[PDB]
Amino acid sequence: GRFTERAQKVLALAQEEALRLGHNNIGTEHILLGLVREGEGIAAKALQALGLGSEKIQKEVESLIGRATIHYTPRAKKVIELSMDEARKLGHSYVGTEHILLGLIREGEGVAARVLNNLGVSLNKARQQVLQLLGNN
Protein backbone atom coordinates (compact mmCIF):
# COMPACT_ATOMS: atom_id res chain seq x y z
CA GLY A 1 0.00 0.00 0.00
CA ARG A 2 1.40 3.35 -1.16
CA PHE A 3 -0.16 6.54 0.15
CA THR A 4 -0.16 10.17 -0.96
CA GLU A 5 1.29 12.83 1.26
CA ARG A 6 -2.20 14.04 2.17
CA ALA A 7 -3.32 10.48 3.00
CA GLN A 8 -0.32 10.17 5.29
CA LYS A 9 -1.45 13.33 7.05
CA VAL A 10 -4.86 11.76 7.49
CA LEU A 11 -3.29 8.71 9.19
CA ALA A 12 -1.24 10.91 11.50
CA LEU A 13 -4.23 13.01 12.42
CA ALA A 14 -6.26 9.86 13.07
CA GLN A 15 -3.69 8.58 15.52
CA GLU A 16 -3.43 11.99 17.17
CA GLU A 17 -7.19 12.08 17.63
CA ALA A 18 -7.31 8.61 19.14
CA LEU A 19 -4.62 9.61 21.62
CA ARG A 20 -6.23 12.93 22.47
CA LEU A 21 -9.46 11.08 23.29
CA GLY A 22 -7.59 8.54 25.41
CA HIS A 23 -7.80 5.53 23.10
CA ASN A 24 -5.00 3.09 22.30
CA ASN A 25 -6.99 1.77 19.33
CA ILE A 26 -7.37 3.91 16.21
CA GLY A 27 -10.86 3.25 14.93
CA THR A 28 -12.90 4.18 11.91
CA GLU A 29 -14.17 7.28 13.70
CA HIS A 30 -10.55 8.47 14.17
CA ILE A 31 -9.96 7.94 10.47
CA LEU A 32 -13.10 10.01 9.85
CA LEU A 33 -11.73 12.83 12.03
CA GLY A 34 -8.36 12.64 10.28
CA LEU A 35 -10.13 12.97 6.93
CA VAL A 36 -12.00 16.13 7.87
CA ARG A 37 -9.11 17.73 9.76
CA GLU A 38 -6.63 17.20 6.93
CA GLY A 39 -8.53 20.04 5.19
CA GLU A 40 -7.09 20.19 1.69
CA GLY A 41 -7.92 16.74 0.37
CA ILE A 42 -10.97 15.68 -1.60
CA ALA A 43 -12.25 13.78 1.47
CA ALA A 44 -12.29 16.92 3.61
CA LYS A 45 -13.82 18.90 0.80
CA ALA A 46 -16.58 16.35 0.33
CA LEU A 47 -17.33 16.22 4.04
CA GLN A 48 -17.50 19.99 4.18
CA ALA A 49 -19.78 20.09 1.08
CA LEU A 50 -22.10 17.67 2.86
CA GLY A 51 -22.49 20.14 5.72
CA LEU A 52 -20.17 18.45 8.12
CA GLY A 53 -17.29 20.22 9.78
CA SER A 54 -14.34 19.20 11.94
CA GLU A 55 -15.83 20.52 15.12
CA LYS A 56 -19.20 18.85 14.43
CA ILE A 57 -17.69 15.46 13.76
CA GLN A 58 -15.47 15.88 16.81
CA LYS A 59 -18.46 16.58 19.05
CA GLU A 60 -20.36 13.55 17.77
CA VAL A 61 -17.43 11.17 18.21
CA GLU A 62 -16.97 12.36 21.76
CA SER A 63 -20.72 11.81 22.35
CA LEU A 64 -20.65 8.17 21.18
CA ILE A 65 -17.37 6.84 22.48
CA GLY A 66 -16.26 9.17 25.25
CA ARG A 67 -12.74 9.07 26.70
CA ALA A 68 -10.70 6.10 27.88
CA THR A 69 0.92 0.76 22.65
CA ILE A 70 -1.25 1.98 19.77
CA HIS A 71 -2.98 -0.14 17.13
CA TYR A 72 -5.66 0.14 14.45
CA THR A 73 -8.91 -1.61 15.17
CA PRO A 74 -9.59 -4.54 12.86
CA ARG A 75 -12.23 -2.51 11.08
CA ALA A 76 -9.90 0.42 10.57
CA LYS A 77 -7.32 -1.94 9.06
CA LYS A 78 -10.03 -3.26 6.74
CA VAL A 79 -10.94 0.28 5.71
CA ILE A 80 -7.30 1.02 4.83
CA GLU A 81 -7.18 -2.21 2.79
CA LEU A 82 -10.40 -1.32 0.99
CA SER A 83 -8.96 2.15 0.23
CA MET A 84 -6.46 0.46 -2.11
CA ASP A 85 -9.30 -1.20 -4.02
CA GLU A 86 -11.09 2.12 -4.28
CA ALA A 87 -7.95 3.84 -5.57
CA ARG A 88 -7.39 1.11 -8.18
CA LYS A 89 -10.94 1.38 -9.48
CA LEU A 90 -10.47 5.13 -9.88
CA GLY A 91 -7.25 4.65 -11.90
CA HIS A 92 -4.85 5.51 -9.07
CA SER A 93 -1.79 3.59 -7.91
CA TYR A 94 -1.58 5.67 -4.71
CA VAL A 95 -4.23 5.81 -1.99
CA GLY A 96 -5.32 9.45 -1.60
CA THR A 97 -7.70 10.99 0.91
CA GLU A 98 -10.76 10.28 -1.21
CA HIS A 99 -9.93 6.58 -1.28
CA ILE A 100 -9.80 6.32 2.47
CA LEU A 101 -13.18 8.06 2.68
CA LEU A 102 -14.58 5.74 -0.01
CA GLY A 103 -13.15 2.77 1.87
CA LEU A 104 -14.88 3.98 5.00
CA ILE A 105 -18.18 4.30 3.11
CA ARG A 106 -17.74 0.87 1.52
CA GLU A 107 -17.22 -0.80 4.88
CA GLY A 108 -20.43 1.03 5.76
CA GLU A 109 -20.55 -0.01 9.40
CA GLY A 110 -18.65 0.73 12.58
CA VAL A 111 -18.27 3.79 14.72
CA ALA A 112 -17.66 6.24 11.85
CA ALA A 113 -20.80 5.02 10.13
CA ARG A 114 -22.81 5.50 13.37
CA VAL A 115 -21.36 8.98 13.57
CA LEU A 116 -22.37 9.76 10.00
CA ASN A 117 -25.87 8.39 10.61
CA ASN A 118 -26.26 10.57 13.73
CA LEU A 119 -24.98 13.59 11.76
CA GLY A 120 -27.64 12.84 9.13
CA VAL A 121 -25.47 11.83 6.18
CA SER A 122 -26.41 9.02 3.83
CA LEU A 123 -23.45 6.82 2.81
CA ASN A 124 -24.68 6.72 -0.81
CA LYS A 125 -24.87 10.51 -0.87
CA ALA A 126 -21.39 10.74 0.65
CA ARG A 127 -19.97 8.50 -2.08
CA GLN A 128 -21.74 10.54 -4.78
CA GLN A 129 -20.33 13.76 -3.39
CA VAL A 130 -16.77 12.39 -3.45
CA LEU A 131 -17.20 11.17 -7.03
CA GLN A 132 -18.66 14.53 -8.09
CA LEU A 133 -15.62 16.36 -6.80
CA LEU A 134 -13.29 13.88 -8.49
CA GLY A 135 -15.17 14.20 -11.75
CA ASN A 136 -15.24 17.99 -11.73
CA ASN A 137 -13.32 20.28 -14.04
Image (tube, helix red, strand yellow):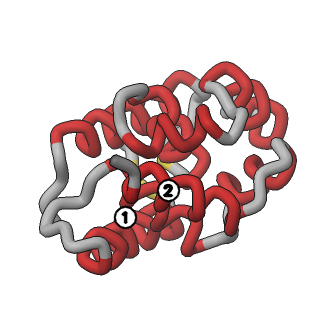
Image location of residue 44, percent across then percent down: 48, 36
User: Which residue type carries mark 2?
Assistant: Gln
Q: Which residue of the protein is positioned furthest toward the front in this rendering?
A: 137
Residue 28 occupies which quadrant of the picture?
Answer: bottom right
Relative horizontal placement of residue 90, taking residue 134 as reference (left or right): left
Residue at left offset 33%, top offset 47%: 137
Q: Is residue 30 left or right of residue 62?
A: left
In this orientation, which residue lies closer to the viewer: 114 or 133?
A: 133
**Residue 89 versus residue 85: which sits nearer the camera?**
89
| 133 or 75: nearer the viewer | 133
Mark 2 falls on what kind of element? helix
1 vs 2, front mark: 2
The x and y percentages for residue 54 are 61, 25
Q: Which of 17/70 is in front? A: 17
Q: Earlier in the sequence, mark 1 or mark 2?
A: 1
- Residue 89, above or below 17: below
Give me the residue at 68% from left, 68% from top: 124
Q: Are marks 1 and 2 in contact (CB under 8 Å)?
A: no
The residue depicted at 59 percent of the width and 63 percent of the height is 128
User: What amino acid type should be assigned to the residue bearing mark 1?
Assistant: Ile
Please tell me which residue is depicted at 28% across the width and 69% down the height of the picture: 87
Residue hosting label 1: 80
Q: Label 2: few (<14), some or many (≥20) within 10 Å?
A: few
- Report the disc number at residue 7: none
Q: Is residue 123 above or below residue 17?
A: below
Left/right of residue 97 with respect to residue 111 in the rendered view: left
Asked which secondary structure carries label 1, the reply is helix
Q: Is residue 19 left or right of residue 50?
A: left
- Which residue is labeled 2 in the image? 132
Reply above or below: 42 against 67: below
